[PDB]
Amino acid sequence: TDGERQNATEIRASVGKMIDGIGRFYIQMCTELKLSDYEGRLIQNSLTIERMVLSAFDERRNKYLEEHPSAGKDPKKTGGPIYRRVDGKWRRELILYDKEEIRRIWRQANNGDDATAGLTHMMIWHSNLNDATYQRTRALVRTGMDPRMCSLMQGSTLPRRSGAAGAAVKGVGTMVMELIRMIKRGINDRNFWRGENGRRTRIAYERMCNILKGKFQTAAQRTMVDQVRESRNPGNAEFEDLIFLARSALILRGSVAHKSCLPACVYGSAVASGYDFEREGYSLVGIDPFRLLQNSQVYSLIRPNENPAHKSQLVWMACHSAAFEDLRVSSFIRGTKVVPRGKLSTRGVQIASNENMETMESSTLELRSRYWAIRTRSGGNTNTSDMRTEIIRLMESARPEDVSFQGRGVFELSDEKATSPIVPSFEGSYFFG
Amino acid sequence: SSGQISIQPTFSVQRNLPFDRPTIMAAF
Amino acid sequence: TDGERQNATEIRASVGKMIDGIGRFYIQMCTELKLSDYEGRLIQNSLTIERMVLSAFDERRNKYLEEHPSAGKDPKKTGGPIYRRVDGKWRRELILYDKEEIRRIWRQANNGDDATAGLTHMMIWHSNLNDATYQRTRALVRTGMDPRMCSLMQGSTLPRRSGAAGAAVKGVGTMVMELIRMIKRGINDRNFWRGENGRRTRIAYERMCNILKGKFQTAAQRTMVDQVRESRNPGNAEFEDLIFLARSALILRGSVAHKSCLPACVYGSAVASGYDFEREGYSLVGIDPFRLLQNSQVYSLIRPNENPAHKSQLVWMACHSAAFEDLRVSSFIRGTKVVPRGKLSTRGVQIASNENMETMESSTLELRSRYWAIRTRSGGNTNTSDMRTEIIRLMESARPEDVSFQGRGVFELSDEKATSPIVPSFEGSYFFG
Amino acid sequence: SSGQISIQPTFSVQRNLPFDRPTIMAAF
RNA sequence: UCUCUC
RNA sequence: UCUCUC
RNA sequence: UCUCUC
RNA sequence: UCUCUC
RNA sequence: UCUCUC
RNA sequence: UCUCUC
Ligand SMILES: *[C][C]([O])[C]O[C][C][C][N]C(=O)C1=[C]C(C2=C3[C]=[C]C(=O)[C]C3=OC3=C2[C]=[C]C(=O)[C]3)=C(C([O])=O)[C]=[C]1
Ligand SMILES: *[C][C]([O])[C]O[C][C][C][N]C(=O)C1=[C]C(C2=C3[C]=[C]C(=O)[C]C3=OC3=C2[C]=[C]C(=O)[C]3)=C(C([O])=O)[C]=[C]1
């Protein structure tokens, strides 16, 4: 590092203040919903609260709902399931809040500031949970992409309203999906790329293709994506080139940011415990999330005949965005063997409406890791016919044995300054296999 | 049967980044 | 030259008085820290002293630290490692000084004057050391720039508080990095370039772009940078133009000032030896630094299994800002073959806290050169679509064989007046390759 | 593999200022 | 080649 | 104010 | 492997 | 085209 | 009052 | 009490 330490501390202060805003907003909403400590630590209650906040600030959807009211749902109220424990058993109740009220509470929590960064953080946490839980092979096959490249679908469920953080965290496969959807839309109707809407669509196409270009690593991919962007009315050839680019990302990996976006319950508990994230600072890639997870208790609803350990592992991988990570390193860091998706005896965290909340129980989630490591936004050792041939040569030269991140290991929770790394010595390796 | 074929390295840890080479290169 | 000799002598007197201030400040601080002659000549002790001085006068960081106190570090004290030799072996101790005390000592050394020029000199020495030691390819890739243009990263670690000297010595690549960071910041948040802060940010953008314009050599680059500056809310097109401008600087080199900013230990030894820099004068580009280095002994700490010759070469290149210079001319001037960075068996000069100061030894640094030469602020023989095509034509016309600095050679240490140059006759040529 | 590609002339000495022409011009 | 500077 | 690993 | 996103 | 005039 | 060649 | 076309 260098004199950029001051810049590195201002960013820490800003992210700490956003975490403080999230936590104290959760505290205020828990007080306004009359939830006890146990219910306030429920992951489903936190998910519902977060979804209500995100729905309250959705400008486009709210405007459309206002202009086209839904069936029996007024466009000025939000809500979701609230799980409250009475006489030992759980019970769900649908709550309804005015969206102006939710926006006012959120603004008051952040000292009268909009703070869209906090909303983006909550959305990224939701996207990480969805990526760690569900496979969207249906959207892959519908768009023509191979369902085998599910490892490139990082941040696929993120809405467009996410800012630069959403673009940074979303993977190459999702960018290819968005571009291919635009290609198909232009193929269906030729009035696309033409007129006043043509300008806006071309601008959006330009911008998404530019940031996909910035996402790649090697020069050949970075030039083929530029060739794809240059075509004014792209057709099947550009779609095929994008397919090839996505396929090449499995070996020539692209740089995708990974951040530890925790559920709002953890931040609320930390703020209630007296932690000042504004003073101490925060970092989504450092020890700060791992340390916070170590000292926090979070409860979750367990469906009948389900394993709490599997659900805790799922929630942990969602928290650390380790859905597509190598299983060996995930198990090494966590200290408990991480079971692939096929052998997880658990369904999604969110509980459907058509469920009987009388055979359901709550289990404490073990969000503890034996070691901690720094999350990276980098790929690995990545060292129109001409570009395709060059890329094929590069992929053929690569092997699944080259060692990447040489000299970088895993640290202990006591090693806050990352002084002494532990290089692992190395079973299954794919989660979604 | 389809499934995950590559690995995306979220953690900065000395690794080998596995991928299923015969199936990926079979497409060309 | 001409009647500007008097002006050329006043500048010499002023820089001599700043060198005298630095040296006698170092002498006073050595007396206040109770360091012997051997410890006073240690390069690590000088680095620590210089860092304490620079930290004491940092207005913005001190104000922020005062308003937001750190964890266990009061914002009114500075310090750093002090290496003292006892019973033959070395030993480190963390020293702590009041910042008011350091400012008072600095002002008393410079006859009650602030003398920010001396602080800028110390900062430039630190920046030259950092450039000669470490590669910031990480900041290059993070900002989107190619990590191949590391030769344009001269003066990258310089803080913003450096005056006109910092802007003169910093390279074209660092200016492009600063501009690109501003571009990215404006792209992320559109409230940039708008409001009261918008005025300040536009003013800073204007000024940095103007001095980048002044840094270039050919008219086409000087006009493209002006085109980039004119856009009120610059976006991706301006960022791409800046990338192209930086890439063109590898062939159409820009004028970057090079100065020999020596460590404070050398100036302190010279002041103790009785040299009057105020009377004799000084010049950061002439023989004065080379002559001073010839007569000075400086010691440095050698880690176990390290080569003192490689560390001495690194310190020499840091002193003369020859990090990005052609290796052939550097070896010709020094008289000893200069080994590229990849084959240097040495780590950085600064010793980390998590090091065992009992297997470490001290070695005398050979800061002697067979010849001496005048450092130049010039490029070489450098003789929106239209501007880009013109620049591409200019770069294609250029070859890596054109002889620049025709008739200008290297002088002997006896030739103080540069009467008889020695044109070298010409192996590796890149340090960071 | 990346690395230094140009030379910045700190010293005022008769030189040729090497640079790797094929790699620099390959970008265009 | 991003072990942290969103 | 919906839901679903493949 | 498309239980709905033409 | 800055072989010294920060 | 930190640290690191790529 | 110096010197140099670009
Ligand atoms: C954290 C950090 O590092 C990050 O970095 C990277 C990122 C950058 N940023 C960017 O790129 C951005 C983008 C965006 C977008 C857009 C724009 C414009 C238009 O038109 C369109 C678009 O689209 C999109 C995006 C994002 C995401 C997605 O997905 C899509 C932005 C906005 O939007 O604003 C910003 C930034
Ligand atoms: C030595 C000699 O020769 C030198 O010359 C050249 C230089 C001149 N100067 C200049 O340019 C300057 C600059 C500056 C700056 C600024 C200003 C203003 C605003 O706003 C902003 C800015 O920024 C910057 C700078 C510098 C550097 C950097 O980096 C950035 C100055 C101040 O600041 O003061 C001065 C001078």
Image (cartoon, coloured by chain):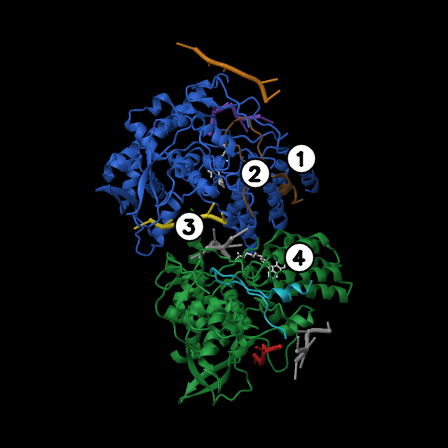
Chain colours: A green, B cyan, C blue, D brown, F red, H purple, I yellow, J orange
Of A179 and A250, nearer the camera is A250
Query: Which chain is mark 1 on?
Result: C
Sort mark 1 into few (<14), some (14-19) or many (20+) by Cα contacts within 10 Å.
Answer: some
In contact (CB < 8 Å): disc 1 and disc 3: no
Q: Mark 2 vs mark 4: same chain?
A: no
Distance from Cα at disc 2 to Cα at disc 4: 30 Å
The answer to whether residue A116 is left or right of residue C299 is right
Query: Which chain is mark 4 on?
Result: A
Circle 3 SS class: helix
At label 3, the amino acid type is Gln
Circle 2 SS class: loop
At label 2, the amino acid type is Ser
Disc sitting over residue C394 in the figure: 1
Q: Mark 3 vs mark 2: same chain?
A: no
Mark 1 vs mark 2, foreground winner is: 2
The residue lying at 45 percent from left, 55 percent from top is A407
- Say which quarter of the image contains residue C7: top left
Query: Which chain is mark 2 on?
Result: D
Distance from Cα at disc 3 to Cα at disc 2: 31 Å
The answer to whether residue C107 is left or right of residue A55 is left
Measured as percent of width and height from the top left, residue C380 is found at 58, 30
In contact (CB < 8 Å): disc 3 and disc 4: no
Mark 2, residue position: D6
Work out whether residue C190 can be spotted: no
At label 1, the amino acid type is Leu
Sort mark 4 into few (<14), some (14-19) or many (20+) by Cα contacts within 10 Å.
Answer: some
Mark 4, residue position: A392
State which tag comes first along the sequence, 3 or 4: 3
The quadrant of the picture occupied by the C terminus of chain A is: bottom right
Disc sitting over residue A6 in the figure: 3
Examine the rendered structure and indicate whether residue A293 appears above or below residue A81.
above
Examine the rendered structure and indicate whether residue A220 appears above or below residue D25.
below
